[PDB]
Image: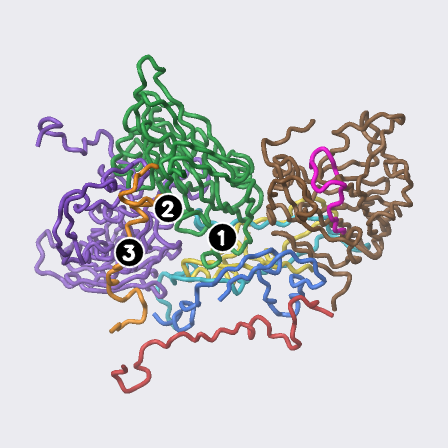
Chain colours: A cyan, B red, C orange, D brown, E green, F yellow, G blue, H purple
Amino acid sequence: PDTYTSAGFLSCWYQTSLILPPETTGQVYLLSFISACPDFKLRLMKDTQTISQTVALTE
Amino acid sequence: INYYKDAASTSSAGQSLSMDPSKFTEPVKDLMLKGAPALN
Amino acid sequence: INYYKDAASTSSAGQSLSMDPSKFTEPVKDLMLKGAPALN
Amino acid sequence: GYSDRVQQITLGNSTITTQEAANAVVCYAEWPEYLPDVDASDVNKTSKPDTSVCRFYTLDSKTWTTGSKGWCWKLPDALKDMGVFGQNMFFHSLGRSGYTVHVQCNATKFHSGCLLVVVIPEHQLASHEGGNVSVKYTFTHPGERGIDLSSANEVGGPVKDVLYNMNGTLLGNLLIFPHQFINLRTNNTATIVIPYINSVPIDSMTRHNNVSLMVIPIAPLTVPTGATPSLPITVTIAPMCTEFSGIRSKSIVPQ
Amino acid sequence: GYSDRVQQITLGNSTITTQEAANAVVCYAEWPEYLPDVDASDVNKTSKPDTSVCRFYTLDSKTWTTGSKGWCWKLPDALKDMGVFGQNMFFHSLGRSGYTVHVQCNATKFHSGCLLVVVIPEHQLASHEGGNVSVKYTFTHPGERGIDLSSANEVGGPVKDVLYNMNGTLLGNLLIFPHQFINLRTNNTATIVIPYINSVPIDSMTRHNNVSLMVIPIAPLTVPTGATPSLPITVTIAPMCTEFSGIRSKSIVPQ
Amino acid sequence: TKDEVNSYLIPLNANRQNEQVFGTNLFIGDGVFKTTLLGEIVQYYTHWSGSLRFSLMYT
Amino acid sequence: TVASISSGPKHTQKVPILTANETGATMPVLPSDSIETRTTYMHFNGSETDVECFLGR
Amino acid sequence: TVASISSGPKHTQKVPILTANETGATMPVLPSDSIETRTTYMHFNGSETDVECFLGRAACVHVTEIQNKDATGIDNHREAKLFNDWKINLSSLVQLRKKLELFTYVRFDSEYTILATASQPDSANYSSNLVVQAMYVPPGAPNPKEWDDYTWQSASNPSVFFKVGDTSRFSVPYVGLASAYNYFYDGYSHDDAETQYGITVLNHMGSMAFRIVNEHDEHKTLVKIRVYHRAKHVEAWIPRAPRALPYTSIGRTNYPKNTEPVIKKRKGDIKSY
């Protein structure tokens, strides 16, 4: 994450509202996915902050 | 120019420039057209 | 002979031999001819 | 597998999808278009902001309850404050526009209720005082809030009696105007495309509204047992083919 | 009978006439043009308000007196509040523009004085504090008022020393930038056409100014005997080929 | 507060009007995005450019 | 190669943005299916994401 | 090519030497417009003033230092110079900086040469032979914390291993995010009231971390790293006035207060020779 280079925000709101049928109750859920369009470019490979270690593993 | 006899000794391979995500993004049995309804 | 695959790895570029100072020395909108009066 | 039923409208940087439409009406069978030269009078070149003004603005939501009488919005007023559409509006002397109106109201297969969604060209309102009392400016320029036909008479405001369309004609005959119904059992949206309708080629956007959009409950809302007794109604509207002309200082309007 | 001397520039709904010009400069010999697709990156269609933004805005006038050090305006800042140009500016994520700058100063055949009118692409100012003190935002966004090089150092503001161009370079070498002189004895206006110059195809109009226009007295004003010792200088500027893209909510900027 | 199947579920409430369902910035290399496959690969590179596809499936 | 084509207003019966994710597919939706776009080119090949490159240092 | 043509007496109504500088032009006047000249040829092409040539020789851009010593009980390797990073810049040593800032935007590939020499300021039996590791750490990569972290595995990050006393050389493509690099930028990273001005993230050329691979010997060894940078494939736009006052900071234009007059005062009159 970098400021100059930042991309925006994504929000979601009720346009009208969720309505449940009779005999039904509680919360309903949305699942959300993300994938890249065919548009996408990635460059200049580097090391990931997502994995590290303190001693070599063994068998 | 390869200076060596064996194939393992050659440098890195060169870009697939293959690229076909459909085996991963659209492995459906009956073809889906964008714009047509998902479930008919 | 380039021994390397990438363009960044090649030696220095070779002389522009472009050279056109008019964008800097004469950026005037109406063309001025040397010898003709500057302001008419 | 195309149904009359599912639709997508993309306009500018905004898109609407409905999975339960009932076709769409195009007023008088004409689609919005720019002002041709043969029809032009003002000699000024006009400004066509295109995608920055021709996108969808969603007005604040209303709440249909069993006591609702109906709501009324005027155009271009309702949009007087939306993004760059509104700025352009206050800044040019003249402007012209068509719109896509999309009214939304979803419920379930146990609800009943039916709204009339109608567009009335030149809807001159009546004073509830009678005689020749006028309807002051502010009252006919409610902005995004629109007029709530179940609100009380106010002074200098219009009459809000529904069986009379706010003008001395019967609710039943509003069907002669481009309109579409939202019947919970069928429909969940209404969409009307409005071409620019005026007796002059371009006009002032602030002293004259050229259509009122009206949403009126006709078959009362009836919710399933022990359901909450109300549904929200949302109105989203997009200017289309907008042109502004005669730019200057920026109008100052009452109130 | 055309002279280099008389000129008319008509842009939008506004026209300028000068009867005492000294040709006009077109930065780097290039005239403003829109953004070609081959150079485009953002996929958004852009908005080109045309004549409503590409007209001439005259900023408030300055007063050249014998003690003046010079003034500095930044673009697009100077126009951040002019008509619809400004609205568009705060409302889109990205925008791009070229300009016609016309600086005016008339006197009589007894006055003397000579102003340098120069456009500096990417004029990064220096803090008068030295070291690595930054120059706060507000200080580099004076708006139509511009910066007055004879005003006092302020805290968080830039240095205002003229022999150093506000950046560690000498006044004498500003002539490498597109510029024109106003020598009372010759000239009464200066006109420079600025093409859009950036390292990206389109940018933010609020976090980055792409040129500073600078008017600097170099040969001091000398009025005839018992004349009032001062002349007003007026700056009129017109955006040209403006395009805005990525419309939304409307930026909020410091102060 | 501990990783759970539940942080994949965006809840929806019946009968709310005008209100907001969720919000997030778009730093694809951090925050919600970071553990997704997209987020996870983006992290092997320094620069990205392109369009993203965000979808919601209703349940 | 175009990265985005030019596309304008839409009012159709053909909605590319409504799908059924239950099917297991990721439908190839693009910016131009839901906003108005302008042409732009890719200027890029995806060279440095080739698996030979990824595992080759 | 002729450098001067032959030209003789003139008595005209056509005066090329009278102009109006107020216009902003520099009219192309020549010796032959105002004296009588003879033909002469140029014999010269202007080869060595090409911008590729001007920015194309190696310049020292950075000197750092690391030491090889027992890290036993060191709580902060970074602080003991057990290892060291450098965020690449071309504006810290002023010689090359003044040269680049003659232009507003610049685009080029870089060729780096890294010379490493060792010093043994206090009593050693010998000179050991150390191998340096230079890792290129792009923004977002884990940064080394100790001199022997998992980071140094550098499985995805380019790193070079060379010997102290030797030199390492490799070349990096133009890594800028935009089309060129702005050594000037009159902007902010966002419209914040207190964000930094001028220093931006589109002049970032990465960053580099150095360490010795060797464990410690009985004495201590100082290794001093010098990074040289050569621009190749240069492209420069918009010339600007040269730097007159001294520099104070990487990335800001700021000059020091109570600096000295930069124009030499005459010893004599305006009339003096």
Work out whether mark 3 precedes mark 2 in sequence or the reverse, and give the earlier one.
2
Q: How far is mark 1 from mark 2, CA to CA?
A: 19 Å
Q: Which residue is drawn at 22% across and 41% down?
A: H12
Discs 1 and 2 carry the same chain letter: no
Q: How far is mark 3 from mark 2, CA to CA?
A: 21 Å
Above or below, F16 against C6 in this view is above
Q: Nearer the viewer, residue E193 or H129?
A: E193
Above or below, D168 against C12 in this view is above
Instruction: Report the amino acid beneath label 1.
Output: Phe
Density class for disc 3 (Cα within 10 Å; few <14, some 14-19, many ≥20) is: some
Residue that carries the numbered disc 2 in the rendered image = H200
Q: Residue at x 35, y 15 (%)?
A: E227
Residue H13 picture quarter = top left
Instruction: Report the amino acid beneath label 3.
Output: Ala
For the residues carrying marks 1 and 3, which lies nearer the camera in this image?
A: 1
Q: Residue H209 carries which label?
A: 3
Residue that carries the numbered disc 1 in the rendered image = F27
User: The residue marked by circle 3 belongs to what chain?
Assistant: H
Q: Where is residue E141 in the image (x, y as percent from the top left)?
A: 43, 34
Q: Give the range drawn in magenta.
A: D192-209
Q: In which quarter of the image is the N terminus of chain H?
A: bottom left
Query: Farthest residue in the top direction?
Result: E226
The secondary element bearing badge 3 is classed as: strand
